Amino acid sequence: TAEVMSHVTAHFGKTLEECREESGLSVDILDEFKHFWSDDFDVVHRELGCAIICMSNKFSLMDDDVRMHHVNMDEYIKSFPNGQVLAEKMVKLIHNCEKQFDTETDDCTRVVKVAACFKEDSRKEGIAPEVAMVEAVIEKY
Ligand SMILES: C/C=C\C=C\CCCCCCCCCO
Ligand SMILES: [Mg+2]
Ligand SMILES: [Mg+2]
Ligand SMILES: [Mg+2]
Ligand SMILES: [Mg+2]
Ligand SMILES: [Mg+2]
Ligand SMILES: [Mg+2]
Image (tube, rainbow, N blue to C red; front, side):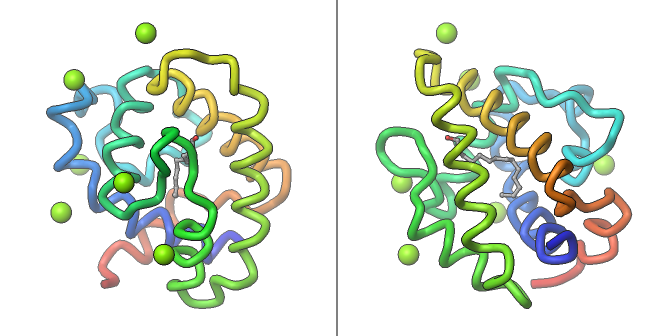
């Protein structure tokens, strides 16, 4: 659900600044990770794919094939309030989007394509939060 997605986003996004330099993710491409969810942000930059790999690896959320680690991602989502309601559905959505991009050879580009698909399908499923709701939880943890 959208409030659970806001907690996951607010926490995951605390690794954006330490991953900017190695990814080339300029503040002029993305200032605050919460903006990922804005109607007005296109999820397309290779640099953002590279940043998400860096961010994921901080929490062991990707496996050695540079794809989501299903058990670690389930356990991470479940670590937030009401997380069990989102954990299976979010793992499913991400993995269905990874299957659509399996022929992309460039890991950074693949990840950003997976991320855009995940945004699209989260919006369609009614679990995409507003930027305001991520902001409301930024102080936690
Ligand atoms: C994790 C909370 C918000 C994340 C937004 C970026 C979406 C990244 C999902 C893809 C995860 C890595 C899988 C790509 O193979
Ligand atoms: Mg840190
Ligand atoms: Mg680099
Ligand atoms: Mg800022
Ligand atoms: Mg690792
Ligand atoms: Mg684990
Ligand atoms: Mg390439």
